[PDB]
Image (cartoon, rainbow, N blue to C red):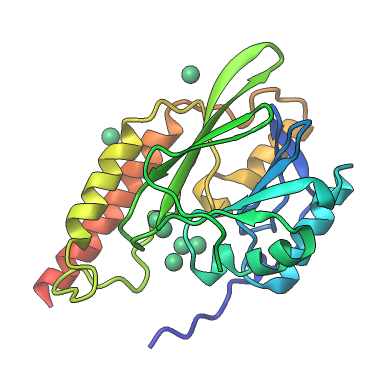
Length: 242
Ligand SMILES: [Cl-]
Ligand SMILES: [Cl-]
Ligand SMILES: [Mg+2]
Ligand code: NI
Ligand SMILES: [Zn+2]
Ligand SMILES: [Zn+2]
Ligand SMILES: [Zn+2]
């Protein structure tokens, strides 16, 4: 069965940086983690694949000039190890409250609003890969220009049973509804959970060369959903033939 070897870049350090507005990238080369800041405290979304990368996230937060003690809320895209594995370490070292859609401190439902000072975020449940998959949205202002931001879950089909799933019986219908929900979200800035899903490394280089809108592409979430759904369709067709 699945050997769960980790691609090398999932645990490879990369320099943290400001993306847009009050959103900062603090993850690894391959696995995203995001710091969203306010004068009343910060949110961290995802923690990388293990306790060691959770420590790396901590040090990226403080390398950007912020205080770890000011992290107040931890959130998640989906609760598998590659995105959630570092959250327990961050929880222990920050005393922050861990939000997880229904060890967690608060459950939440679809359209839940998270507010912390200037931070306003909205959870959009996007079940499929797991029943708890959560995509997050927010908005920022960058050089006086308003921008909408979406943190989609991974839209993965890795290890999913799509025909005769006895656990998640509605899995195919959930995926298809989640695809539709994500398409219906206007999104100037898509910030995905894996580097290759957003070309984040190359965008960071564009930014260092002076591109002020390197992360802005209002068509990208539609293109990501379309690509994830094509891969979903292919895997579904394979499992149906077998
Ligand atoms: Cl996913
Ligand atoms: Cl994934
Ligand atoms: Mg827009
Ligand atoms: Ni389309
Ligand atoms: Zn997963
Ligand atoms: Zn992943
Ligand atoms: Zn998902």
